Length: 461
Ligand SMILES: [Cl-]
Image (cartoon, rainbow, N blue to C red; front, side):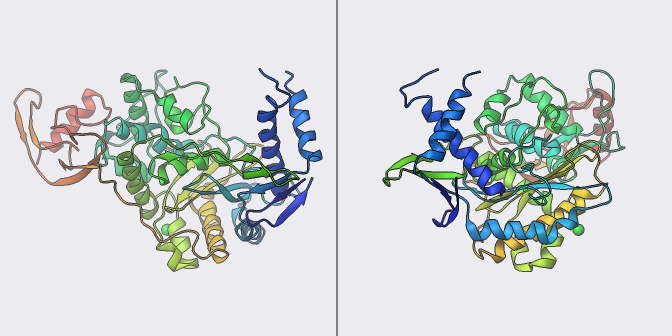
C-alpha cells in the first residue's frame, strides 16, 4: 500500500502530508466497511480499526489531489518566511489551505511552523472562531440571496445594545451612523451584522440550511453575536470551503485530499464523487465577489495588496477578493483570499489561546500570506489564473439614492409627506424587481432616535 501526489509520484508507503492523507483514506474505507462484511448501522472503534488494518495490509495505491511542486513551495515559504509572524508574544502558529475552486480539491497546505518541533495540524485539526470572516457567509450573503438587501443598501451602525444591555462594540467604539454595505464590510463594523442576522430571524430564514450545505456544524443558531463568529469554531480546511463556494459563483464542491484508491490488481476501488450544490444563487455570489474585491483594495483591515504589489506586481494585478477576522482579544487572525481559480485560507494564533500583537492580522499575516502566494506562483506560473470575477447576467441593477439605498420618491417625514431627491448610485440585487421605493425605515436596523437624527440631515439637503 502507498500514497502518491497527483502526478503519480510516491509520497510514501504505510510529515503532515502523510498523516493527513492516511487519515482521509482510512475514513474512506471505514465508511465503506460499514458495508463490505455486508455490515450495517461506541463500536464503531472496531470498524475504525478494521479500516486502518484493511488499508495497511491491502496492496492499495492511494492518489492524492496534492500538487507536488506547489505543496513543497508552500513548505519552503513557511520555513523561509514564518518569522514574519513572530511579534514578541511567543510562538505564533499558522495553518493554510489551497483549494481548487472548480473541484474542491486541495493542492497544498501548511500544517504549522515546523512539524519536528510541534505536530499539531493547524490546517485540518484545530478549530477556532472564524470571527468577522463569518459575516459574508452567514449574514450579508444570505440577506442578498433572500432578496432583503442589495450592494448599496444602507445599514444602521448607531450605538445599540445586546438583550442584556451590554453595548455592541467595535474595539473601543460604540457605533457611528448610517452606512452602505460597502462600508460595513471594508471596516468590518459589527452592529450592522447584528441587525442583518436579526432581520434574517424575524423573517424565518433557514440560515442553517445554507451553512449545512457547505458542511458547517454550528450547535446553536439562536445567538445574537453569531454573525461575528460567536458560538462557532472551524478548521482552516472547512473554512476555505465556505470561501470556495462564493469564489465559484455560489456552487459548493466538497473538500477532499484523495481522488482515487486502487487495488493491487489496478481496479479502481474508491473515486471522489462530485456532488455540486448551488448554495447561493449566481446573482448573490457574483455580487458578494464585487464587495469582497473592495475589502482588499481599500486596505482598511489588511495590507495584503500592498505587500503583494512589492513582491510580484504582475500577480498583484490578478482579480483578488478576500476577507479578514480578529477574535475579540486579538487571539486569532484570519485572512481568506480568492482569484477565480483558487482560494487560500489562512489562520494565525497560539496553541494556548492567548493574545497576539495588535497588528498581527492587519500587517503580519497579510505580509506572510503575500510571500506564500508568490512562492505558490513561482512554482506553478499559471495556477492563480488571469480571469476576472464578473457580475452574473441575472443580477438586477437598480438606480437608488445614495442616502437611502432605495429608489427616490415621497416619504412622510414625521407627518408632512416629503419629496426625497439627490445623488444616486447603481445597486445590485439578487431578486426579481430590484430595490424598493424609499420608505421611512430605509436601513437595516436602527431605533426611532437614530432615524430622527438620520432623516434630519437627509432633509437638510
Ligand atoms: Cl497598505
